[PDB]
Image (tube, rainbow, N blue to C red; front, side, top):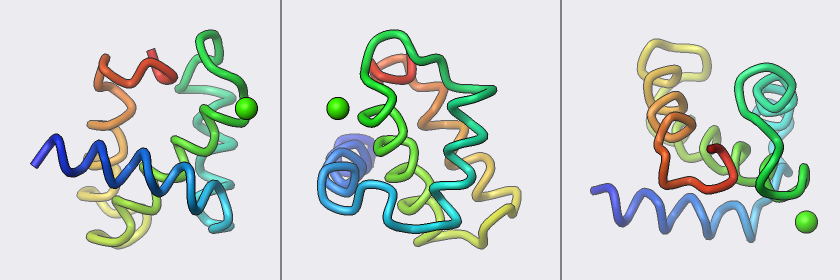
Length: 84
Ligand SMILES: [Ca+2]
C-alpha cells in the first residue's frame, strides 16, 4: 500500500542511490525534462527518482506500460516534496 511504497522508496533512495545504470539514465532524462529541480538538491532528487525506477522495475519490465504507470504515479504524487 501507499505508506509501504513511500517508505521502501525513501529507504532505497538513501541506501541504493543511483547505483543501477538503467535507472540512473532514465532519471537523468526525467530531471532534465519531467521533474523540476527547485526544492531539493540535484543529488537528492536524482536519488529519489532512481529509487522510484528501481522499485517499479522490481515489479514490472523496464519500459513496459506498467513500469511507465508506476514511475509516473510516484513522480506525479504531490507529497514528494522533491518532485513538486
Ligand atoms: Ca544532497
